[PDB]
Amino acid sequence: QFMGIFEDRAPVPFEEVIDKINAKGVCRSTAKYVRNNMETTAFHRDDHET
Amino acid sequence: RRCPTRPEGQNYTEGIAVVFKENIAPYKFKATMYYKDVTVSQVWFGHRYS
């Protein structure tokens, strides 16, 4: 059973928009962003950055 | 002088008419929604409050 599903939208940083998405055509698997006055990072699949 | 007489006059065809305009109203019908609100609440019970 689901006890809860926290869904959020995080911005893609400038250094990821230019250097990753626009240059290589890929996106990082980790979201590092400021939410509720705190720096939070989420790793996809609870794995390493890819 | 030989001056002209009254014009011929318009010939009118008596009849019946129905005037249709473009349809803009959406097609409406009756539907039924079956669903379930699943609400799972996490409560922390303090000393004097919840």
Image (spheres, rainbow, N blue to C red):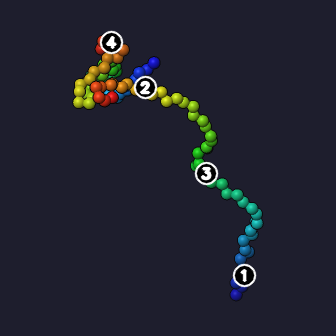
Q: Is residue A19 above or below residue B30?
A: above
Residue A45 on image: x %, y %: 36, 14
Looking at the rendered image, the disc whose residue lies closer to the viewer, 3 or 2, is 2
Instruction: Give the number of the disc on residue B40.
Output: 2
Residue shown at 29% from the left, 25% from the top:
B46
Residue indicated by mark 4: A47
Residue at 23%, 30% (x, y): give it: A37
Extreme-bottom residue of the structure = B1
> Which image quadrant is residue B47 in?
top left
Q: Is residue A35 visible?
A: yes
Which numbered disc, 3 or 4, marks the residue closer to the eye? 4
Looking at the image, residue A7 sits to the left or right of residue A38; the answer is right
Q: CA distance from mark 4 to mark 1?
A: 101 Å
Nearer to us: label 1 or label 3: 3
Whether tag 2 and tag 1 are in contact, CB under 8 A, the answer is no
SS for tag 2?
A: loop
Q: Amino acid at mark 1?
A: Thr
State how far apart marks 3 and 2 are (Cα).
50 Å
Query: Which of the pair A37/A19 is nearer the observer?
Result: A37
